[PDB]
Length: 385
Ligand SMILES: CCCCCCCCCCCCCC(=O)CSCCNC(=O)CCNC(=O)[C@H](O)C(C)(C)COP(=O)(O)OP(=O)(O)OC[C@H]1O[C@@H](n2cnc3c(N)ncnc32)[C@H](O)[C@@H]1OP(=O)(O)O
Ligand SMILES: COc1cccc(CC(=N)NC(=O)c2ccc(Cl)cc2OC2CCNCC2)c1
Ligand SMILES: [Cl-]
Ligand SMILES: [Mg+2]
Picture 1 (cartoon, rainbow, N blue to C red):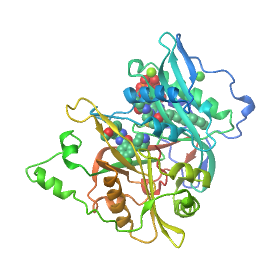
Picture 2: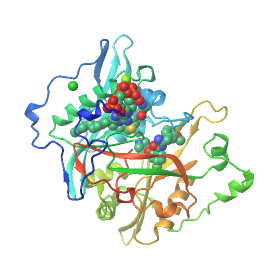
Picture 3: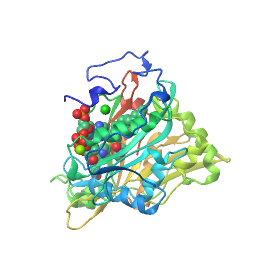
Picture 4: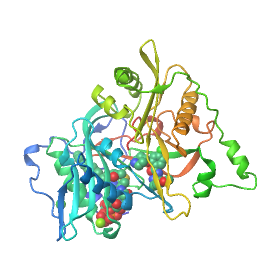
């Protein structure tokens, strides 16, 4: 609650509130020529390390660090378990910098004990498009917590981003920091009810016996949009047009190039699933979701919760409810146990009807070095990884 580090950074104070007409950096007229050229100082016996995410072995090291040390749910039952291949896709998007993929090693073990990453992306906030970094995967080894490593990681990636004449960033966290531009609850749609019950993800009452819970969450194996199919390279221009058009209504969204569309949407097994409805060689409807397993900590029977996370979903030929009903069936068809979605975009309107349950927390959206009015999650049009 003191935010001793955060309060030194160009982010709003916890009591700052800005008019709708304020939409600008906290610190303008920055100069690349003035940016520190020296790496930030690490504690004795630790070293910066530039990770090559395209090298299987370096990628494996980041994977291991995240598997053992990344985000857990509030009750420490689950831990996110991003796959190696997901990390490769997440970090090697168009115009990515290797030098924004930053490790820290303990010199004596040669072991990776900290990470932070960013990728470039054009972000439209309140109708101004700004070159930004999207920051993700900040992680410090569980054995080294509350030693103020995280601010060094932050300050070092800020410096390397600033060297590229980028002065804004976007990120998200579960934790409250100075100061969200928006705050979105997450919801879950049970698919394998029994499993989710057995692992303590979901529960039963005397009203809801096991057979009744299973029957509740039953879906028909038949698509509302019969032609919905895996996206193909030929669809890239059609998706770019459909998605790009739709995203303009929002207060915060990424501005995608065709190269970014192909990267972010072309399907990769166990990473990203995009489906399209093509009519007359035109893309009219799209569904997408990414795969993010959680490791189930100390359950005798199951080791992994497979989960699909709603990415971007646009319909022009069905209702948004029918579209999302199809997104659920498609995730069931891909052996997911649960479908997760944030109350962003049009999502919340379908949660009651599609039998989504409210989850235990929320995801806060932040900008660095940007001053603007905050807004309700309906007005958020971007989903980070
Ligand atoms: C223009 C370019 C700008 C680029 C940069 C943009 C900004 C990018 C910012 C990064 C966005 C990343 C987004 C992202 O990856 C998605 S959110 C996921 C973050 N990762 C985890 O939660 C994994 C599990 N936790 C850990 O590994 C550690 O607890 C971490 C490393 C989180 C904190 O390590 P620690 O050992 O627990 O703590 P200290 O070293 O003692 O440091 C304490 C200081 O860290 C502040 N803190 C804690 N969690 C934070 C978080 N999630 N964002 C930002 N700040 C966070 C905290 O408030 C405190 O500052 P304060 O005293 O002022 O309160
Ligand atoms: C069930 O396993 C979990 C494992 C770890 C943490 C949690 C609880 C949680 N924090 N959930 C979510 O943040 C989350 C829950 C639902 C959704 Cl739709 C998105 C979420 O965040 C994602 C996007 C930001 N980067 C991480 C993925 C759940
Ligand atoms: Cl400093
Ligand atoms: Mg620390």
